[PDB]
Each structure stands twice: as structure tokens, then as C-alpha cells.
Amino acid sequence: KVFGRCELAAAMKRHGLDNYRGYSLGNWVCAAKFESNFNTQATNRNTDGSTDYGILQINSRWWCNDGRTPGSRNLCNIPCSALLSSDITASVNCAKKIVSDGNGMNAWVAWRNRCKGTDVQAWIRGCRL
Ligand SMILES: [Cl-]
Ligand SMILES: [Cl-]
Ligand SMILES: [Cl-]
Ligand SMILES: [Cl-]
Ligand SMILES: [Co+2]
Ligand code: NA
């Protein structure tokens, strides 16, 4: 599923991301934009052989099982395919674990490079939520 901007913001708020670990909703929307272009089915192979899955491009090296990432972990206790669902619950729940892991949203390089410090509120502007 490719979400619209405001549709994703609303879904993210419903699932508890607004101000989660202090990160306003716009931060999460911005991260998803640059990670996946709001597409739940997005997958991208990483140089290390792991793969990123879903709207927040969660990586198989640590967070989910895809059966093809040697020496990796599955800290969210989910098949990586669960992260590709039109329902974002699994991605949100796993993202909550990631953002709690110590480095906050810097865990997403795209957030650090393209969202951090910018006017992230613009991502939820005009939305009914
Ligand atoms: Cl957009
Ligand atoms: Cl915001
Ligand atoms: Cl594996
Ligand atoms: Cl933080
Ligand atoms: Co990535
Ligand atoms: Na894994």
C-alpha cells in the first residue's frame, strides 16, 4: 500500500507514534517519506547483505527474520514480511523498539540526514487528525 501523507500521519498517531520517545509526528512522517516514499511494500538490500523492509525500512540485521541474513538477530520477533503489510501495526511496534534502543531516531540514517533539525511539522500541515 502507498499511503498518502495525511493518511499515514493519522495511522501513525492512532498507533502511538505522536511524541513517542519525544519525537513529534512530523519526524515519523518525514522518516517514512525518505525511507520508503510511503510504500509499505518497499524493500532494499544493504551492502552488508541485510535487507530493509517496509514503510520505515527496518533492517533484517537486527530487527526481523528474513532467513537470509547471516549472524543476524530478530529483536522484534517477526518475519520481515510482516513489515510489508498494508496494516502498519508491526512496523510501528518494531519502530518503537528501535527508537528506544539508545540513539533515538538517529537509528534511521535518512532521518538524521534529511529530517533532523528541519521544520518537520510541515509534514502534518493541513491534515485532519
Ligand atoms: Cl508527500
Ligand atoms: Cl511535528
Ligand atoms: Cl537470517
Ligand atoms: Cl532521543
Ligand atoms: Co536503511
Ligand atoms: Na534477522
Image (tube, helix red, strand yellow):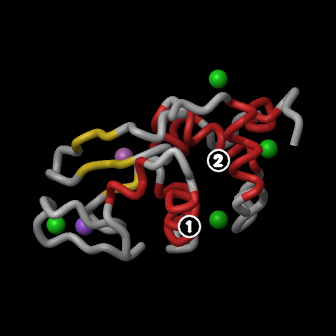
Q: Residue at x 72, y 36 (%)?
A: 7
**Position in image of residue 28 (x %, y %):** 64, 47
| Disc 1: which residue | 93
Q: Residue at x 55, y 40 (%)?
A: 32
Q: Above or below — where is 25 with respect to 99?
A: above
Q: Secondary structure at mark 1?
A: helix
Q: Residue at x 22, y 60 (%)?
A: 66
Residue 99: percent from the left, percent from the top?
56, 65
Whole-percent x and y of residue 76?
Answer: 42, 73
Image vertical order of residue 61 relative to residue 127, above or below: below
Residue 116's x, y, as percent?
A: 63, 43
Vertical position of residue 99 compared to residue 7: above or below: below
Q: Is residue 40 left or right of residue 126?
A: left
Amino acid at circle 2: Trp
Q: Quadrant of the C terminus?
A: top right
Three-letter residue code for mark 1: Asn
Mark 1 residue crowding within 10 angstroms, few (<14) / some (14–19) / many (20+): some
- Which residue is drawn at the image coordinates 16% and 64% (left, top)? 67
Element class at badge 2: helix
**Number of residues whose C-alpha sits closer than 10 Å to that of mark 2, classed few (under 14), some (14–19) or many (20 or more):** many
Dot placed on the residue nearer the N-terminal end, 2 or 1: 2
Counting every numbered tag in the picture gives 2
* Numbered label attached to residue 28: 2
- 103 or 44, which lies in front? 44
Ligand 6 neighbours mark 1 (CB distance < 8 Å): no
Tell me the distance, in whole angstroms, between the alpha carbons under discs 2 and 1: 13 Å
| 126 on left or right of 46 | right
Give the label, 2 or 1, closer to the camera: 1
| Residue 120, placed above or below residue 62 | above
Mark number displayed over residue 112: none
